[PDB]
Amino acid sequence: LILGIVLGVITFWLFAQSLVNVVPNLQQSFGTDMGTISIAVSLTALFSGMFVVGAGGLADKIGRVKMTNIGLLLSIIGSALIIITNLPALLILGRVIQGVSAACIMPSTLAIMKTYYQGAERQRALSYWSIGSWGGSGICSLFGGAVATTMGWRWIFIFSIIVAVLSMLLIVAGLIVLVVMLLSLNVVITKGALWFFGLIAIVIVAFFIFLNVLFENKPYTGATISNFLLNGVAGTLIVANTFVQQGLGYTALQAGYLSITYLIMVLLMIRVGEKLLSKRPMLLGTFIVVIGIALISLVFLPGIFYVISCVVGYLCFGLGLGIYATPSTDTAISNAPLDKVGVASGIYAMASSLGGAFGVAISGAVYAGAVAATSIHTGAMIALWVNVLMGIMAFIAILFAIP
Amino acid sequence: QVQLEESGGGSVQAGGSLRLSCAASGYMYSTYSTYCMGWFRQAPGKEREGVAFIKRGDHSTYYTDSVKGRFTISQDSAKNTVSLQMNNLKPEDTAIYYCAADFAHSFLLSVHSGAGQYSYWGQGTQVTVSS
Ligand SMILES: [Zn+2]
């Protein structure tokens, strides 16, 4: 019950991020119009990504498993509060704590992996953690839909409380001027503007105030900075899933089959990434993905049987992330000092999250800009090429992560 | 930063034909998701009413009782656009036809109709029929 408990806590952050793609079913029950009822659901990550460091630090100080006990307990009220009562001002209050739930779990449960294992076992521990995250988030959209169509929107949150219990049953030093920075920084990526120019200021401001209110010169720094750059290519699938479905006029399933082919491939290479192990496999992963992008880029100048070039790309892309993820979850969790893991793990978890947001936003904006100026096929390449640059910068980012 | 650019419609005699085409610029699909797209009409007197809708993922369509059989919504997949082909029109169909699309959702979830569920709206294309 080492991973069996940890995974149960990670999969509490699956059933949270499943309702996000069932936002219309909630529209009926909770009543209030979309935009307000949608942003309500968004709050779960918004608050998670900003608090992860603080909730990691208050786990670092006042007990690791203490905060994993809080998070798993806070996930019960997080779900029970929503599933039971169907009204709007209610939903907001439940999604915000569903977010802090994750902020407590991710860093703390990541620190337990260091204690429980302490080398050699850490390889099998962090690999099981990756399966719990990648595989969990990987289906969350495909899950939430399957549940809402047949069981219901509330029947995805009855699975949240029981798995959160079966997890526990199978086992302010400027924080406020960091969350104000990260609140701003998170909503800056969501660019709906003229007015966002001043919203970039509050980020730069609250950054330098927290900067003058933390002396890492380890390979852990190299792993975190590379992990950020590497997750910048996250847009690749979003821009690909679009191109395939709009440009090549495929159905929803074939798009999902290309995607779930990537999913199983990345899930059966975090295991092989474990055996691969530190710096060597992380260079192979960050490399082979860039070819995986190029393989999906060249399907913008294709033939009739160029579906292969796209397919082999999804595998090439999938397997590369897998070969990088287990070694690089370990290179960080290793050098992270036992005295300060909860704070260190939260930063690695934050850096991973911001990387994805920063990536997708660029990938989308470029695609939306390029496809307007030129066409779908031409525009896709311009967007896919921008993913290559970050993938190469992710391969160059390993240069500052010594053996 | 999505723009529903819509075209077609116009004036015609009763029991005639009028195409209505609409396309969504830079509306990307999530990792396992799609969106629904269709038209709502609103005559100068009557209140807003849904016409025809299609889910872009699996070409799953839905119509209002009024137009059913006469109207046919579909998407010209290679050219990336939804178009409502309206036939045997009657003076009831005379109204401002607004193209709309809802926030992305898992393609598993069923096609949408209710104006509250749809979020993106267009300027509106006029269609009028007479003797
Ligand atoms: Zn829809």
Image (cartoon, rainbow, N blue to C red):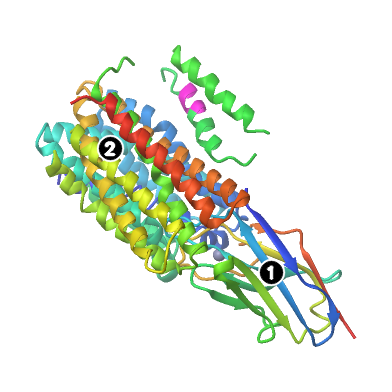
Q: Quadrant of ligand 1?
A: bottom right
| Residue toward you, A40 or B131 | B131
Which residue is the site of mark 1? B21
User: Which span is picked out in magenta?
Assistant: A176-181
Q: Amino acid at mark 2?
A: Thr
Whether residue A180 is in magenta: the answer is yes
Q: Which residue is mark 2?
A: A68
Q: Secondary structure at mark 2?
A: helix
Image point (33%, 63%), residue name: A308
Q: Quadrant of residue A219?
A: top left
Mark 1 touches mark 2? (CB < 8 Å): no
Horizontal arrangement in the rendering, residue A375 relative to residue A322 (left or right)? right
Q: Residue at x 76, y 63 (%)?
A: B124
Residue farthest left in this picture: A120
Mark 2 is surrounded, within 10 Å at the Cα level, by few (under 14), some (14 to 19) or many (20 or more) other residues, namely many
Chain for numbered disc 2: A
Residue A276 point in image, percent of width and height:
14, 42
Q: Chain of mark 1?
A: B
State the count of labels: 2
Q: B41 or A41, which lies in front? A: B41
Q: Quadrant of residue A287?
A: top left
Instruction: Judge the density around disc 1: few (<14), some (14-19), many (≥20) Cα neighbours within 10 Å.
Output: many
The answer as to whether callout 1 falls within 8 Å of ligand 1 is no
In the displayed orientation, state which residue is furthest to the right: B131
Foreground mark, 1 or 2? 1
Q: Quadrant of the C terminus of chain B?
A: bottom right
